[PDB]
Image (cartoon, helix red, strand yellow):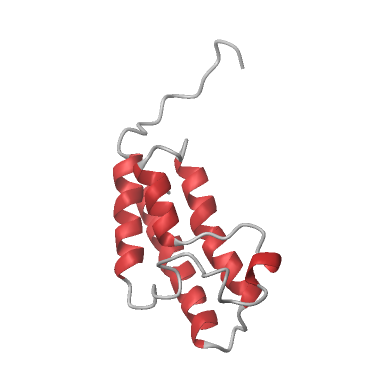
Length: 115
């Protein structure tokens, strides 16, 4: 509350560390469905169904331009990428499996870096 604070966690490396995680996600062999925004002109149903499209290149631009106020807002966008994927793709599809794999990959890096 006012004048009552938990000890100050060092957040000075968060930006660099989120960048590193994101590089690792970008270079994963199963990243290909997520690298670029879904083409809303060419994929029927995507625009209407997925109310908040997100992809790694969009995260990278937001990260590089100071648009994440904290590491939780960064995680929220990464998770959004996989939540969107699950919304639109059957589990038993290459893309559906890619999304599950990448989410797992992400969550482990996240826990290991920050928890």
